[PDB]
Amino acid sequence: VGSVAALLTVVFYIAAVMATNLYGATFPEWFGDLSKSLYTLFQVMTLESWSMGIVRPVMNVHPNAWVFFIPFIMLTTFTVLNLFIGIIVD
Amino acid sequence: VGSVAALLTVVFYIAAVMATNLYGATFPEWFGDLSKSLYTLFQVMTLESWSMGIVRPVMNVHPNAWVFFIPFIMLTTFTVLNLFIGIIVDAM
Amino acid sequence: VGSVAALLTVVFYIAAVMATNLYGATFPEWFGDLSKSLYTLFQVMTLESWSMGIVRPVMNVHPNAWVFFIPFIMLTTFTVLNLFIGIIVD
Amino acid sequence: VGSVAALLTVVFYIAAVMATNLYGATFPEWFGDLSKSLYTLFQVMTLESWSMGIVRPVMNVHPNAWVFFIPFIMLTTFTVLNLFIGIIVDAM
Ligand SMILES: CCCCCCCCCC(=O)N(CCO)C[C@@H](O)[C@@H](O)[C@@H](O)[C@@H](O)CO
Ligand SMILES: CCCCCCCCCC(=O)N(CCO)C[C@@H](O)[C@@H](O)[C@@H](O)[C@@H](O)CO
Ligand SMILES: [Br-]
Ligand SMILES: [Br-]
Ligand SMILES: [Br-]
Ligand SMILES: [Br-]
Ligand code: NA
Ligand code: NA
């Protein structure tokens, strides 16, 4: 559980670093700095307007953006369930 | 677990083949080609703007679209839950 | 499990009957007939735009609408988890 | 289980008392009185338009609003999961 939450924070920070560099210049409101990118990736993790509000607008400039976002959603949500269920048992 | 992930991929692919055919011509931005259709059905599976942003606009042209999307949501949502729980149990 | 799904269908139909009578006249696009109301209550059960898209617009005309919608969400989602987990075990 | 449902109600009430105070004057439609604040925090807890529709507009005026809402989502989401699983286990 402790190791699970550690992995989640590292992946979240690494993903927000990547997102800042990729979309920061073209999408400054969402990815303009590390802070903004961490906030956006949390919104995306919660699945709130991820496609209609974030990813589809991002894909209009960067067609391959889904290669970042879809694996991120698959990875962070699977980890979150694993962490939530893992903490409940212990 | 592997068979579940295989079944989900097959079901997902056929669903996007069907959706391209049904809505492609009338909704090209969301279902105009297999790629776009795989992306939309993923958005639909996550439940993101599925009704307000996709299914209701689709229902304006195709009144029965709900016969496709509602069973799709029910089928994939039950499977993704079963798959994610399946990995957790088969690791404890 | 079989009894759980039976209860869910009855509550869903009864709720869609109630919604048609309550909001049908003022909100015809969402609750104008039993069919429309069943579709809307499914959208509301999945939590998609339930407040921003449906309930807040409904509350502008019917201030107490939340007394219908909030218990519905609480009831149908709890039942759905109970049914999903219940089927997985058996 | 009962203690969990009690803790959630207390946490929910205090959160809506705080939100009324912090955002009431600047966001009256969503946090203008305790009632509106209880309703908004329920919408936020379900994750419905929490960021695009509530938290980002709130962050335009109050840049630190995320310090309130993100821990709120994390706290209530973990509790609601724990409460719902808790009833299921304490019936099997
Ligand atoms: C899982 C761990 C999730 C951690 C989430 C961390 C969020 C950090 C957000 C932050 O530090 N901000 C700067 C606060 O000064 C908020 C930004 O999101 C903000 O600059 C922009 O979004 C603006 O557009 C808002 O008007
Ligand atoms: C858990 C069980 C969920 C069951 C869901 C049943 C849905 C039945 C929907 C239906 O029969 N319709 C009529 C099909 O002719 C669709 C309506 O939703 C439609 O009339 C309106 O929404 C219009 O506004 C669309 O343009
Ligand atoms: Br969360
Ligand atoms: Br998912
Ligand atoms: Br569902
Ligand atoms: Br809920
Ligand atoms: Na949503
Ligand atoms: Na959701």
Image (spheres, coloured by chain):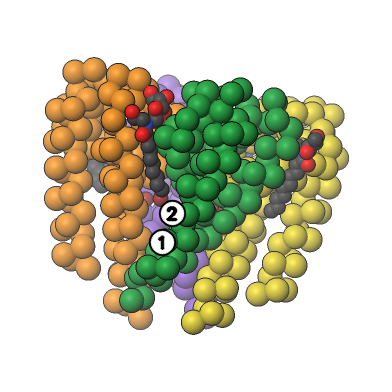
Chain colours: A purple, B orange, C green, D yellow
Q: Is residue B10 visible?
A: yes
Q: Chain of mark 2?
A: C
- Closer to the camera, B79 or B86? B79
Q: Amino acid at mark 1?
A: Ala
Secondary structure under tag 1 reads helix
Residue denoted by label 2: C9
Q: Is residue A19 visible?
A: no
Q: In the rendered image, which quarter is residue D24 located in?
A: top right
Q: Is residue A24 above or below residue D46?
A: above
Indicate if the residue with disc 2 has its beta carbon within 8 Å of ligand 2.
Answer: yes
Q: Is residue D41 left or right of residue D26?
A: left
Q: Position of residue D25 (x, y in %)?
A: 84, 29
Q: Residue at x 37, y 68 (%)?
A: C2
Q: Position of residue A22 (x, y in %)?
A: 38, 32
Q: Residue at x 35, y 60 (%)?
A: B81
- Closer to the camera, B32 or B18? B18
Quadrant of the rendered image holding ligand 1: top right
